[PDB]
Amino acid sequence: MKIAIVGVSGAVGQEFLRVLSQRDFPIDGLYLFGSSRSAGSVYSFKGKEYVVRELKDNDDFKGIDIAFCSAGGDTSIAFADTITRHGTLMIDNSSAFRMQEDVPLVVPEVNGDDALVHPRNIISNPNCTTIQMVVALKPIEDLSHIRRVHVATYQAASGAGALGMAELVQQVEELARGEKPTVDKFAYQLMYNLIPQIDVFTDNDYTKEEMKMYRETKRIMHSDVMVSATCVRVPVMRAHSEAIWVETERPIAPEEARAAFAKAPGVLLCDEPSEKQYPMPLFGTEQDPVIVGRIRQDLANPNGLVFWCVSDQIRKGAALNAVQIAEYLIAKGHF
Amino acid sequence: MKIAIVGVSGAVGQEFLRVLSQRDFPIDGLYLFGSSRSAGSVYSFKGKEYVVRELKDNDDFKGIDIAFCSAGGDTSIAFADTITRHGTLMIDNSSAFRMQEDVPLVVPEVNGDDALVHPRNIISNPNCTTIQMVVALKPIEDLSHIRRVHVATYQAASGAGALGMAELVQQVEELARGEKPTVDKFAYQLMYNLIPQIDVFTDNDYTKEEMKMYRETKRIMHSDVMVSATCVRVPVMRAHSEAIWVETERPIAPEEARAAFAKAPGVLLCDEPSEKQYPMPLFGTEQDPVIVGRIRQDLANPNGLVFWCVSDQIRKGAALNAVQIAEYLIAKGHF
């Protein structure tokens, strides 16, 4: 198996290097690609050193089985033709192709079989916050169909990439020193604040991030489910939190939901109120599961269930999900 | 008018001193009370200095018209008899009496007339997060009855008093210095974290804070409304944030809701997506209004409305609401 990483310089591209090693992904050849800014940089992987090639509209992807791309939708749109020119399967972290009906939109725990059919040899990774939500929703859906979801997100600085993380940390230093906080990558100061806007606004006054949770969830779950989200930036480094109300066609008691979560792939149940055990982003950082807790009945709806969950944006929210798609296809004999 | 402040040492008691001066509350005599820890301390108010008396089970409240108490439910339960012994009206910030049916539970913008009848000469201030929610809910209720509310809160360190605020600030310093964060007043590190537990758990696995939003809202709004809350501690100093989904008996369009908010007492509309204008706790800090924005239709419910709002926990969430109750009674000739 010959593997490409397109966009290796950033937080997610570095996570691909870590995950692919940690999970002993089968690799006979590794090929790193980036923009002219990253061309010529050196990275070591499993005891050997690799030199980044500039992504050009040529034949560099001949012989490459899978290309994991974390270079942004700009690059994916412009170079998808190049990457797939010689039969390479492009697993795209970008939002570029997520609404194309001939592009599968995959979370392996939920709709892994959708990955098997990729007429454009493109598969798209969903948005971070969608991935974490549907991993939690799938075990509930299997009990009784989910009609409606209200979700409030508490989303980390990593959503704005490594520069967003660095801005938050520098604000902590400036504030401790009594200096003015530098504000740049976020629209307002983030330390000691909450910004109830992630991505640009759309015509219905939801942001693009909130509409992704509406549109992508339907595709992934093959569902008429309607998700209304309020997505808020919070002073957390790289794990996202979600407060979720789910309405099902029949009531699900917390004990039935708890039993389903305890058996669900990709989920870690952490729900012991008497021990103050609940998901928190600081402890879900750099961990694989979607961590679920605060499970209770919905006081406002007899058909409602309420819970809280956490996942790492860089792992399950990005690179881990993409590797798990690739592992799923390997496991079904696709290669 | 002779006015007492019971529990003047803490953040809310100091806010009473500021608010009562700023709003030119009519004061002929001021009397400060606290525990033995605060007895003998000096505070200046409108150009004169006052010495704190220890709260004792005696006749110190003879001649006092109103006692604003911010000393915790322990003190209010123990000394309510003393404070009211000579006809003084006790306006209590504590949770002690909030479910006593002969104790009115008042937000002046919503049910001010309930304050006029106080057989025990006690009126209770509601919980911070309830106050901010019902100030926003009242203009929507007047359009169409609210049946159900889902609310996710993003609650500031000030909920844990001045020591909670000081713990957050010290964690910012320790983290900037690369030291271990001291953890004490909160159950876990709060900086770079979110704690989805405020107050102790109850038998239905909601916390006491979440159940206050259920129970107090019904009392204040004279309503069968059912509120299901997830209350989360966030790294913010003293302003609370709430993500709210409201279901009404008929659909309310965002433009109708916007018009109602723009005319509502105690509300400040801040909702211009194209200008990135929305409520944020950093800018609602040390301000009076409940700031409301991100108003949109609920994609999951044709009878749903979604919005976001912010208020200062120490002002409208505590001392300002209590002073406004007292001002309401003065204005109705009660004294």
Image: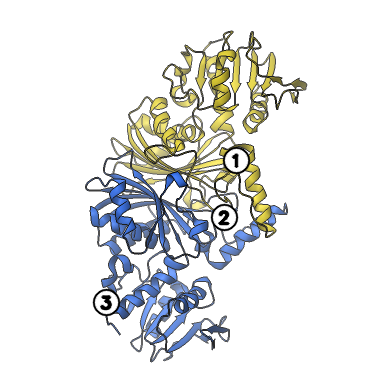
Chain colours: A blue, B yellow
**Whether residue B199 is visible:** yes
Residue A60 appears at what percent x and percent y? Answer: 43, 90
Q: Residue A116 — which label?
A: 3
Q: Residue B192 — which label?
A: 2
Residue A177 appears at what percent x and percent y? Answer: 73, 54
The residue mark sitting in front, 2 or 3, is 2
Instruction: Give the chain of mark 1.
Output: B
Instruction: Give the chain of mark 2.
Output: B
What kind of residue is marked 1? Thr
Q: Which residue is mark 1?
A: B285
**Whether residue A94 is visible:** no
- For image coordinates 65% across by 19% down, the residue present is B55
Residue B309 appears at what percent x and percent y? Answer: 48, 41
Quarter in which the N terminus of chain A is drawn:
bottom left
Q: Earlier in the sequence, mark 1 or mark 2?
A: 2
Gap in Å between the C-alphas at discs 1 and 2? 20 Å
- For image coordinates 47% across by 26% down, the residue present is B109
The residue mark sitting in front, 3 or 1, is 3
Quick check: do tags 2 and 3 share a chain? no
Give left or right: position of B50 versus B313: right
